[PDB]
Image: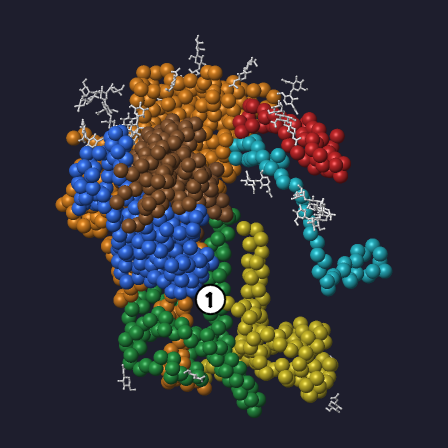
Chain colours: A green, B yellow, C brown, D orange, E red, F cyan, G blue
Amino acid sequence: FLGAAGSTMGAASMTLTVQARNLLSGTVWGIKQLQARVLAVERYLRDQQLLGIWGCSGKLICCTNVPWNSSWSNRNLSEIWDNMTWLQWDKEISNYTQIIYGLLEESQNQQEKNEQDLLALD
Amino acid sequence: FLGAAGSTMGAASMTLTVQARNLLSGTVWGIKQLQARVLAVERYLRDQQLLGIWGCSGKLICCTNVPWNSSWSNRNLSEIWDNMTWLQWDKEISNYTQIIYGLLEESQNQQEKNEQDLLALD
Amino acid sequence: AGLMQSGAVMKNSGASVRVSCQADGYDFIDYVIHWFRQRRGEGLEWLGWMNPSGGGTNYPRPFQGKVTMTRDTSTETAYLDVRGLTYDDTAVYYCVRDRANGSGRRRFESVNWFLDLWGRGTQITVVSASTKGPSVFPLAPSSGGTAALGCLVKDYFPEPVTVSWNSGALTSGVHTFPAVLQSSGLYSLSSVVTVPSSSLGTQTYICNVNHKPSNTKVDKRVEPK
Amino acid sequence: LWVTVYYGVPVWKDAETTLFCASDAKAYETEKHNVWATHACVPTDPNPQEIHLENVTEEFNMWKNNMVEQMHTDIISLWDQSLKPCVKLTPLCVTLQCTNVTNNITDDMRGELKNCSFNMTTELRDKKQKVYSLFYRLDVVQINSNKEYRLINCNTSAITQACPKVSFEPIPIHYCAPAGFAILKCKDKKFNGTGPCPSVSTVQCTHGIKPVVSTQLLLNGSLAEEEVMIRSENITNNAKNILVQFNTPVQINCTRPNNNTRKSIRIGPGQAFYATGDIIGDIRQAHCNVSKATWNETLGKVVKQLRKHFGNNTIIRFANSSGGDLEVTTHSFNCGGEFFYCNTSGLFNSTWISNNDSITLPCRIKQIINMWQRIGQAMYAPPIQGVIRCVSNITGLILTRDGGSTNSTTETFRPGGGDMRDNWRSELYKYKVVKIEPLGVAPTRCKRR
Amino acid sequence: TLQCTNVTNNITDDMRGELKNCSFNMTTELRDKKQKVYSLFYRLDVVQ
Amino acid sequence: IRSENITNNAKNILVQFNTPVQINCTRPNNNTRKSIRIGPGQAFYATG
Amino acid sequence: ALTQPRSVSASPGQSVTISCTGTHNYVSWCQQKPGQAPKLLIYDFNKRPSGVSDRFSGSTSGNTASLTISGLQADDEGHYFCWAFENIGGGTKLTVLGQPKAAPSVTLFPPSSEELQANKATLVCLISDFYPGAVTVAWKADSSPVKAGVETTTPSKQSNNKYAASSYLSLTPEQWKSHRSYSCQVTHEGSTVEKTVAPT
Ligand SMILES: *[C@@H]1O[C@H](CO)[C@@H](O[C@@H]2O[C@H](CO)[C@@H](O[C@@H]3O[C@H](CO[C@H]4O[C@H](CO)[C@@H](O)[C@H](O[C@H]5O[C@H](CO)[C@@H](O)[C@H](O)[C@@H]5O[C@H]5O[C@H](CO)[C@@H](O)[C@H](O)[C@@H]5O)[C@@H]4O)[C@@H](O)[C@H](O[C@H]4O[C@H](CO)[C@@H](O)[C@H](O)[C@@H]4O)[C@@H]3O)[C@H](O)[C@H]2NC(C)=O)[C@H](O)[C@H]1NC(C)=O
Ligand SMILES: *[C@@H]1O[C@H](CO)[C@@H](O[C@@H]2O[C@H](CO)[C@@H](O[C@@H]3O[C@H](CO[C@H]4O[C@H](CO)[C@@H](O)[C@H](O[C@H]5O[C@H](CO)[C@@H](O)[C@H](O)[C@@H]5O[C@H]5O[C@H](CO)[C@@H](O)[C@H](O)[C@@H]5O)[C@@H]4O)[C@@H](O)[C@H](O[C@H]4O[C@H](CO)[C@@H](O)[C@H](O)[C@@H]4O)[C@@H]3O)[C@H](O)[C@H]2NC(C)=O)[C@H](O)[C@H]1NC(C)=O
Ligand SMILES: *[C@@H]1O[C@H](CO)[C@@H](O[C@@H]2O[C@H](CO)[C@@H](O[C@@H]3O[C@H](CO)[C@@H](O)[C@H](O)[C@@H]3O)[C@H](O)[C@H]2NC(C)=O)[C@H](O)[C@H]1NC(C)=O
Ligand SMILES: *[C@@H]1O[C@H](CO)[C@@H](O[C@@H]2O[C@H](CO)[C@@H](O[C@@H]3O[C@H](CO)[C@@H](O)[C@H](O)[C@@H]3O)[C@H](O)[C@H]2NC(C)=O)[C@H](O)[C@H]1NC(C)=O
Ligand SMILES: *[C@@H]1O[C@H](CO)[C@@H](O[C@@H]2O[C@H](CO)[C@@H](O[C@@H]3O[C@H](CO)[C@@H](O)[C@H](O)[C@@H]3O)[C@H](O)[C@H]2NC(C)=O)[C@H](O)[C@H]1NC(C)=O
Ligand SMILES: *[C@@H]1O[C@H](CO)[C@@H](O[C@@H]2O[C@H](CO)[C@@H](O[C@@H]3O[C@H](CO)[C@@H](O)[C@H](O)[C@@H]3O)[C@H](O)[C@H]2NC(C)=O)[C@H](O)[C@H]1NC(C)=O
Ligand SMILES: *[C@@H]1O[C@H](CO)[C@@H](O[C@@H]2O[C@H](CO)[C@@H](O)[C@H](O)[C@H]2NC(C)=O)[C@H](O)[C@H]1NC(C)=O
Ligand SMILES: *[C@@H]1O[C@H](CO)[C@@H](O[C@@H]2O[C@H](CO)[C@@H](O)[C@H](O)[C@H]2NC(C)=O)[C@H](O)[C@H]1NC(C)=O
Ligand SMILES: *[C@@H]1O[C@H](CO)[C@@H](O[C@@H]2O[C@H](CO)[C@@H](O)[C@H](O)[C@H]2NC(C)=O)[C@H](O)[C@H]1NC(C)=O
Ligand SMILES: *[C@@H]1O[C@H](CO)[C@@H](O[C@@H]2O[C@H](CO)[C@@H](O)[C@H](O)[C@H]2NC(C)=O)[C@H](O)[C@H]1NC(C)=O
Ligand SMILES: *[C@@H]1O[C@H](CO)[C@@H](O[C@@H]2O[C@H](CO)[C@@H](O)[C@H](O)[C@H]2NC(C)=O)[C@H](O)[C@H]1NC(C)=O
Ligand SMILES: *[C@@H]1O[C@H](CO)[C@@H](O[C@@H]2O[C@H](CO)[C@@H](O)[C@H](O)[C@H]2NC(C)=O)[C@H](O)[C@H]1NC(C)=O
Ligand SMILES: *[C@@H]1O[C@H](CO)[C@@H](O[C@@H]2O[C@H](CO)[C@@H](O)[C@H](O)[C@H]2NC(C)=O)[C@H](O)[C@H]1NC(C)=O
Ligand SMILES: *[C@@H]1O[C@H](CO)[C@@H](O[C@@H]2O[C@H](CO)[C@@H](O)[C@H](O)[C@H]2NC(C)=O)[C@H](O)[C@H]1NC(C)=O
Ligand SMILES: *[C@@H]1O[C@H](CO)[C@@H](O)[C@H](O)[C@H]1NC(C)=O
Ligand SMILES: *[C@@H]1O[C@H](CO)[C@@H](O)[C@H](O)[C@H]1NC(C)=O
Ligand SMILES: *[C@@H]1O[C@H](CO)[C@@H](O)[C@H](O)[C@H]1NC(C)=O
Ligand SMILES: *[C@@H]1O[C@H](CO)[C@@H](O)[C@H](O)[C@H]1NC(C)=O
Ligand SMILES: *[C@@H]1O[C@H](CO)[C@@H](O)[C@H](O)[C@H]1NC(C)=O
Ligand SMILES: *[C@@H]1O[C@H](CO)[C@@H](O)[C@H](O)[C@H]1NC(C)=O
C-alpha cells in the first residue's frame, strides 16, 4: 500500500493494485463519518467518470490517441521512469492539467466514437 | 451546456459532451443538500446501470441489435434530425418507453452474451 | 470599532491605580492583549501581555510584581494595575491587540507579533499631593546677540499659571514655555523676553505672575549683574 | 510520445477532511449502559496495519495541523452531549446560611469547606425543604448578617449536574480516516514539530489516545525517546507557549484523603440531587506526591536540552505562575471524577546553571466548572464517598518564557497553558492528513485501435 | 402583574402616553429575592 | 402586474415596479438599554 | 533596543527612507498620528495587507531594516516606529518640508543668586524659533555629559509657527561649583550647537 512512492516510476509501475485495494476496502457524531464515506464514494465516482468519458474506462492503464507537447517541460525517456517519482511529476504538471483533461474528454472519444459510428455502420 | 435544445436533432448531435460535464462537475439545513447530492448520485448510477445492462455501457452512443416498430409513429429519415427536437421526441415516446427498455435489457445482452459464450468457448 | 482607553489621570508617589481597555467589535476571548508605555520623550517600552483565555501572562523581568494586568471575560474588558508609583512612571499607556497569537481557529499568522488594534492610550501623571504656590527666580541677561532675560517659576502644582510683563503691558518678544514635570512630581516653567542692548539701565523689567489655585500673585524685579 | 494514464498512483497533497474515531473491543464490554461517550465508535483494527515508506520526505507542521481542532470541536461537542439530558440545578441559586467546620483537622484544613443550610423544592411544588450540605470554599461567595453565601456561577451561568453514571476516565481512542485520505506518520524521534520528516510510515488508524485533561502538567501521555523533546512554533516568540515531551515517565500519586458521604436529595420528581454529607473521621487536604530525584534528573536532562537554543551557558530560572484563573495558575485536572487544582508553586522555585523524602504538593478540590470558557453552562461535579487515589505518569509540560530584554543574559520559565489544544498537539505532533489522487498520466509511444 | 403609568415629557398628544412606564417584581440572579424594577413599552405590548 | 386569475378578486394582485420608490423611515428617539439580571446566564434587555 | 532616527523631514510627493537597526528578526512598522490610535502598516519586513496604500514599501538588509515611502502626503504627519518582538524602536517624528530649515536659537542661563540663597542650583537651556520642531539635547559638566536629574520638554507652536522648547538641569550649588565648564548642547538636524556657563 503506497509502498515506496520514492522508488522511481519504472520500479513503481510493477503493481498498481493495492492503492486501488484499500481505496474502498469493503445521532450527531454519527452523521459525520456518513458525511465522509459519501464523498469518498463521490471522489471514486468522479474518478470513474473522468475515466469512462476518456477512451480508458478499461481500468488502471490506457493508451491514448494524443501525443506530447514540447513546451510542457521537454525532457527524456530514462530521466523519468528511472530517476523521478509521482508527486515529483504532478507538482510540475500542476500548471497544465486542465487543458490536458479538456482535450482528452473532447477531441478524443467524441471524434473517436463518431468515427467509429462511421465504421460501425458498414 | 444544453445550448440549443431547439436546434434540430442532427445539429444537436455534434456535441454530447457538456450536458455530461456539469452533470456532476467535481446540522439540519445542512442535512438537505446531502439528501439532494445523494439522489443525484443515485440517478447517475441508475443511468449507468440501465446503460451497462444494455450492450451499450460504452459511453454516450451505442448501436443495438433491435430495429423499429411501424406503429410506433411511422415517419421519415429527414423529418426528425432536420425538423425535430429532443423533448419533442420523448413526449411522443412517453407512450412506449417501458417495453422498449424491457426488450433491450432482456432480449439483447442476455441472448447476446450467451451466444457469445457459445463462441467464447471455441 | 477599536478600543476604549480610560482618560488621563493624576495620582501620587507610592499609591496604586487601575486602568481600563474596553474591547468592542470582535472576540474578546480569541487573540491576545499587550500593554506599552512612552515616558517623557522616550523610546516606547513593553509592559506585559495577557492571553484572555485561561488568563496566563508574562511580565518582563524588571516589571514583575510591579504590574498586575487582568481581564473580565463577561464585561469583555481588559484591566491593568500599577503599584508603588514613582515619577519614573509618568507616561502614556496603551493596550493593544495581537491577532497572530491567542486561542481560536482564526489567526492571521505572522512571525512578528501583530499590533493590529490600538487603544488611544491613557496618560498617567504622578503628582505629589497638596498644591504649593510656586517659586519665582529672575534670569537676567549679561555678556552681541541682543539682550534677553526672563523669570522662571518652579516646583508648583497644578498648572496652569499666569505670567505677565508689567501688568502684561509689554507683549513684544515674549514667550512662555511649556510646563515641566520634574521628578519631584511638581511643575516648573519660565517666561522670557528679549530686548535691545541699550534697553537695559534705562528701561527696566519685572514679572507679574499669579497661581490663583493657590491664590498667590507675585511681582519680581529682574536685574542683570 | 503519446499519453497514458494510471489509476492508483502515489500522489497526494495538503488537505484536511472529516475523520472518525475507533475504540477497540475490550472497552465495549462493561455492562452498565453507555461509557465515556463513544456510543457508536467502531472497534480497532486488531493488527498494526502500517506501511513504511522508502525514500520519501515531506513536511509536517504540528501547528498548521487540523485533526487537533477536529478533536477539540469533537470533545466540546460530546461535552455538551454528556450532560445534555443530565439533571438540572436551577433551584440552587438560593441563599445559603452557612458556617465552617467542627473537627480537629488543623488550620491546614481550616474551614475552607462550608456547612450551608437552606430551603429547597421538594418532590412536589408546595413544600419547601430545609436542608444542608458541605462545599469547597471556591464554590461559594459572600454577599455584604450571619453567613449567607451564593454559588459562584449564579451571577453568570446556569449549571447542570452530570449524570452520576458518567465516569471521567480517558480511554485510548484510535482516530481513523477515510480512504482517499492518508495519515503520514513521522518515525524519527528528533522532530521539533516543524519541517520535513524523512523517517515515515503511512497509517489510517492512529494509536489509542487518552485525551488527558490537565494544565501545566501533561499526564499519561506519550513518551519521547533518547534526548527529551521540546517544541515551539517559534520560541523566540516568547508568547508562543512551549510544549515539551518526556522520554522519562514521572511517577505521580494524587490523593483526596477523606471519606465522603452522599445525599440523594429529592428535588423530584425524577431529578434527584446529590449532595455532600458529613465526612468520616479526620479531614486532610488532597495533594500529590512525586519522586524527588527523578524530578531532579528529568529537569536536569531538560535544562541540558534547552541551552542549545539559548547558549550552552545561560542563566535559567523557574517560578510559580504569572497569575491566572485557577485552571491555569495551578495544575488543574480531574482524577476519579472530582477535580483538583494543585499548587505547582513548590516544584519551580529554582535557578539553573550550566552542564530525602518525596515532594508533597497540595491540591484543592472544586466541583463547579464551565471549562473551555464555555460559560452559559456549568457542570456540578458530584461527590464521591470514600477516598480518592490516583496513579499517573507525567510526560510533558506547557511553559512560558520570560521576555527579559537583554541579548541572551537571563531567561526564566514558568508553567504556561490555558489553551487546551496543546495537550492534543502534544500527541498530534506526529501526523499529517494527505489527500491522495489515484490518477497520474504520462507521455509514451503507445497507440490505440 | 405590571403597575404602570404613562409619560412625563413635552412630546404632544401626537406621542401622548402610548409608551408605558411599568413597574413590577422579578426573579433575581438567585431564586429567593424578588426584584422591583420598571421598564417602558409600546401601547400594543400591554393590555388592561 | 400579475394575478393567478384577477377576475377572481380574492386572488391578491402582485405588482412589480420598473421604478424604485425612495422611502426613508425613522424611529426618531434616542433609547437606552437595561441589562436586567434575571440570572444566572439569562440576561434580560429592557427599555430605559 | 532599535535605532530609528530622531527626526526626518521632506517635501510632499517625494520618496523617503526610515531606517531601524538591531537584529535579523522580523521587523514591522506602525504609525502615530498625534492624538490618534496607532495604525499598523507593514508586517514581516516587506508586505502591506488590507486597507493600506501601496505607497509604503518595507524592506531590509539584515540587522538593518527600512521603510521607503512613495508620494509624501502630509495627512501622514507624525511619528513612526518599528519593532521586533519585545525589542522596540524609539520612535521617529517625520515632519514635512514646508518652510525653511530653521536653525534654532539656544540660550543658557545660570542659577539665580537667590537660588543659591535657597541652595538649589537650577540651570536652563532654551531653544527658540526653530524648525522642524525636532531636536535633542544633552548636557556637559566641564568635559563630561550627565545622567542625573535632567528634564526636557516637547517642542511646540510659537506665535510664529516655529518652535520652542526648554531643558532644565537641577543640581546642588556645590555640584555646580565642581566642574566649571558647565554647558548645554543641542543637535538640530545634524548640526550640533553648544553654549557654556562657568561659576562666576
Ligand atoms: C505523601 O507524602 C506525605 C508526607 O510524607 C504522606 O504523609 C504521611 O502519611 C502517612 C499516612 O497517611 C503518615 O503515617 C502515619 O505515621 C504516624 C506516626 O508514625 C511515627 O511514629 C511511630 C512511633 O510513634 C513510628 O514507629 C513510625 O514509624 C513508622 O514508620 C517507620 C518507617 O519510617 C516504620 O518502620 C514503623 O513501623 C512505623 O510504621 C507503622 O508501623 C506499623 C506496621 O509496620 C503500624 O502498625 C504503625 O501504626 C506505623 O504506622 C513513625 O515514625 C502513625 O502514627 C500513623 O499510624 C496511625 O494513625 C493512623 C490514623 O488513625 C492509622 O490509620 C494507623 O493505622 C495508625 O493507627 C501513620 O502510619 C505519615 O506520618 C505522613 N507523614 C510522613 C512524613 O510520612 C502521605 O501519606 C503521602 N501520600 C501519598 C499518596 O503518597
Ligand atoms: C420627514 O418629513 C418631516 C416633515 O417635513 C420632517 O420633519 C421636519 O423635521 C425637521 C428635523 O427633524 C424639522 O426641522 C426643524 O425646523 C425648526 C424650525 O425651523 C424653522 O424656523 C426657522 C426660524 O425660526 C427657519 O429659519 C427655518 O428654516 C430652516 O429651513 C430653511 C429651509 O426651509 C433653511 O434655509 C434655514 O436655515 C433653517 O434651517 C436650519 O438652518 C441652520 C443651518 O442651515 C440651522 O442652524 C438651523 O437650526 C435651522 O434648523 C425653519 O423655517 C428648527 O428650529 C429645528 O432646529 C432646531 O431644533 C432642533 C431640536 O432641538 C435642533 O436639533 C436643531 O439643531 C435646532 O436647534 C429643526 O431644524 C422640521 O421643522 C420638520 N418639519 C418640516 C415641515 O420640515 C422629518 O425630518 C422628515 N424625516 C425624514 C427621515 O425624512
Ligand atoms: C453541618 O451543619 C448541620 C446543620 O444543619 C449539622 O446538623 C445538625 O448538627 C447539630 C449539631 O451541630 C445536631 O444537633 C444535635 O442533634 C442531636 C440529634 O438530633 C441531639 O441529640 C442534640 O441534642 C442536638 O440537637 C443536629 O441534630 C444536626 N441535624 C441534622 C439534620 O444533621 C451537621 O452536624 C453539621 N456537620 C458538620 C460536619 O459540621
Ligand atoms: C493514568 O493511568 C493510570 C493507570 O491506570 C490511571 O490510574 C487509574 O485511576 C483510575 C481512577 O482515576 C482507576 O479507576 C478505578 O479503579 C478502581 C480499582 O482499579 C475501581 O474500583 C474504580 O471503579 C475505577 O475503575 C484505575 O483503576 C487506575 N488504574 C489502575 C491500573 O488501577 C490514571 O487515572 C490515568 N490518569 C488519569 C489522569 O486518569
Ligand atoms: C508565587 O510566589 C510568590 C513569592 O515567591 C508568592 O508571593 C506572595 O504572595 C502572597 C499573596 O499575595 C503574600 O501573602 C501574604 O502573607 C501574609 C502573611 O503570611 C498573609 O497573612 C496574607 O493573607 C497574604 O497572603 C506574600 O507576602 C507574597 N510573598 C511571599 C514571599 O510569599 C505568591 O503567593 C505565589 N503565587 C502563586 C500563584 O504561586
Ligand atoms: C418611569 O417610572 C420610574 C418609576 O419606577 C421612574 O423612576 C423613578 O422616578 C421618580 C420620579 O418620577 C424618581 O424620584 C425622585 O428620585 C430622585 C433621585 O432618587 C430624588 O432626588 C427625588 O427626591 C425623587 O425621589 C425615582 O428616583 C426614580 N427611580 C428610579 C429607580 O429610576 C422613572 O423616572 C420614569 N421614567 C420616565 C421617563 O417617566
Ligand atoms: C428556610 O425557610 C424558613 C421558613 O420555613 C426561613 O425561616 C424564616 O426566615 C426569615 C428570614 O428572613 C424570617 O423572617 C422568618 O421569621 C423565618 N421563619 C418562618 C418564615 O417561619 C429560613 O430563613 C429559610 N432558610 C434559608 C432560606 O436558608
Ligand atoms: C507509566 O509508565 C510506566 C513505565 O514503567 C508504564 O509501565 C509500562 O507500561 C507499558 C505499557 O503498559 C509496558 O509496555 C512496559 O513494559 C511497562 N514498564 C515496565 C517496566 O514493565 C505504565 O504503564 C505507565 N502508566 C500509564 C501510562 O498510565
Ligand atoms: C468510609 O465510611 C463508610 C461508612 O462508614 C465505610 O463503610 C463501611 O465500611 C466497613 C469496612 O469496609 C464495612 O464493614 C461497612 O459495612 C461499611 N458500611 C457502609 C454503610 O458502607 C467505609 O468502609 C469507609 N471507608 C473505608 C476505606 O473504610
Ligand atoms: C507512588 O505510588 C507507588 C505505588 O504506590 C510507589 O511505588 C512503590 O514504592 C515503594 C517504595 O517507595 C515500593 O516498596 C513499592 O514496591 C512500589 N510499588 C509500586 C506499585 O510502584 C511510589 O514510590 C509512590 N511515589 C510517591 C512519590 O509517593
Ligand atoms: C502555594 O505554595 C506557596 C508556598 O509553598 C504559597 O505561598 C505562601 O503564601 C502564603 C500566603 O499567606 C505566605 O504567607 C507565605 O509566605 C508564602 N510562602 C513563602 C515561602 O513565602 C502559596 O500561597 C500557595 N498557593 C498558591 C495558590 O500559590
Ligand atoms: C526554594 O528552593 C529551596 C531549595 O534550594 C528550598 O529550600 C529549603 O530551605 C528551608 C529553609 O530555608 C529548608 O528547611 C528546606 O529543607 C529546604 N528545602 C530544600 C529542598 O532544599 C525552599 O523551600 C524553596 N522555596 C519554597 C517556597 O519551597
Ligand atoms: C412587588 O413586590 C412588593 C413586595 O415586595 C409588592 O408590595 C406589596 O403589594 C401588595 C399588593 O397586593 C401589598 O398587599 C403589600 O402590602 C405590599 N408590600 C409588601 C408585601 O411588603 C408590590 O406590589 C409588587 N409589585 C408588583 C407585583 O408589581
Ligand atoms: C443618545 O444618548 C447617548 C447617551 O446620552 C449619547 O451618548 C453620548 O454621545 C456623546 C456624543 O456623541 C458622547 O460624547 C458621549 O460620550 C456618549 N456617551 C455615552 C454613554 O454613550 C448619544 O450620543 C445620543 N445620540 C446621539 C445621536 O448623539
Ligand atoms: C503546445 O504548447 C505550445 C506552447 O509553447 C503551444 O504553442 C501549442 O499550441 C501547444 N500545442 C497544441 C497542439 O496546442
Ligand atoms: C536527453 O536526450 C538528448 C537526445 O534526445 C541528449 O542530447 C541529452 O544529452 C539527454 N539529456 C538528459 C539529461 O537525459
Ligand atoms: C409492434 O407494434 C405492433 C402494434 O401495432 C404490434 O402488433 C407488434 O407485435 C409490435 N412488434 C413486436 C415485435 O412485438
Ligand atoms: C416520407 O417518405 C415517404 C417515402 O418513404 C414519402 O412517400 C413521403 O412523401 C415522405 N413524407 C414526409 C412527410 O417526409
Ligand atoms: C470561618 O472561617 C472564616 C475564614 O477566616 C472566618 O472569617 C470565620 O470567622 C470563621 N467562622 C467560624 C464560626 O469559625
Ligand atoms: C522565527 O522568528 C525568527 C526571528 O524573528 C526568524 O529568524 C525565523 O525565521 C522565524 N521562523 C521560524 C524559526 O520558523
Compared to G156, does B3 lie above or below?
Answer: below
Q: Quick one: label 1, few (<14), some, or many (20+) residues within 10 Å?
A: some
Nearer the observer, D323 or C159: C159
| Res. G66 visible in picture | yes
Q: Position of residue G84 (x, y in %)?
A: 31, 52
Q: Horizontally, is D441 left or right of D250 in the view?
A: right
- Which residue sits at x=28%, y=35%? G112
Q: Residue furthest left?
A: D355
Compared to D140, does B73 lie above or below?
Answer: below
Pointer 1 residue: A44
Q: Position of residue D273 (x, y in %)?
A: 49, 27
Name the residue type under label 1. Answer: Tyr
Mark 1 CB within 8 Å of ligand 15? no
Q: Horizontally, is D274 left or right of B61 in the view?
A: left
Compared to D128, does A39 lie above or below?
Answer: below
Nearer the observer, D99 or E21: E21
- Numbered disc 1: what chain? A
- Which residue sits at x=27%, y=38%? C225
Q: Classify residue A89 by image quadrant.
A: bottom left
Q: Position of residue D289 (x, y in %)?
A: 25, 32
- Mark 1: secondary structure: helix
